Length: 97
Ligand SMILES: [Zn+2]
Image (cartoon, rainbow, N blue to C red):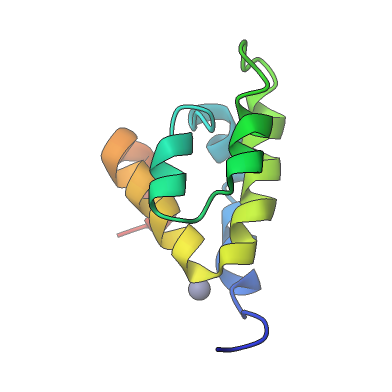
C-alpha cells in the first residue's frame, strides 16, 4: 500500500482536453458505471445528480475529474472505458491511438 499517486501526469493531460471533455461527457449519466468501477463515491453521485438540467455540465465534469484523480490511474482507466463505451470518436481524440 503506497501513500500518494504520481497520476498528476495522467490527469494534467486531460486538462489539455477539458474544453471538449466537460462539453461532450454526461457526468450524471455514467454515475452507476463509475461507482461500479469503484472510482466515484455515493456522496459525490448525489452531488453530481443534484443538477437535473445539466446546463452546468461544463463545470460538473471538471469538478468530477478533480475527485477521480484521488483514485489514481484506476479513475483514468474507468474514464477511458466510459469514453470507449459511450463516445467512440471522443475516445480516439483523448487516448490518441
Ligand atoms: Zn497514471
